[PDB]
Length: 64
Image (cartoon, rainbow, N blue to C red; front, side):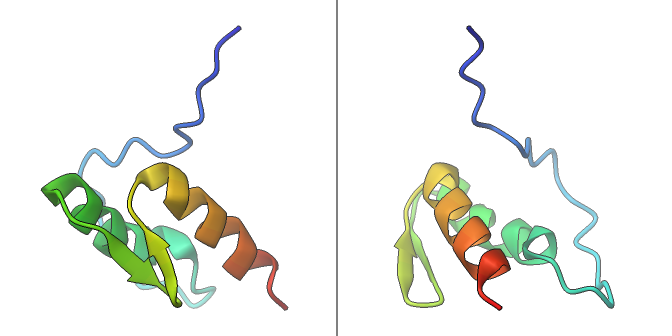
């Protein structure tokens, strides 16, 4: 019932420069490769889809 993994639409994106530094800012650059028809290797992890971007999102964000 509603298997909606898409947590980000990516309409365009303002592409901000936050003091916090969030993967949101990086995802506007990163996903732009994925939607163009290539794969971007983020932090040595080969991201091919915005689904693969969710793994490097959570793993890098949890990496204290």
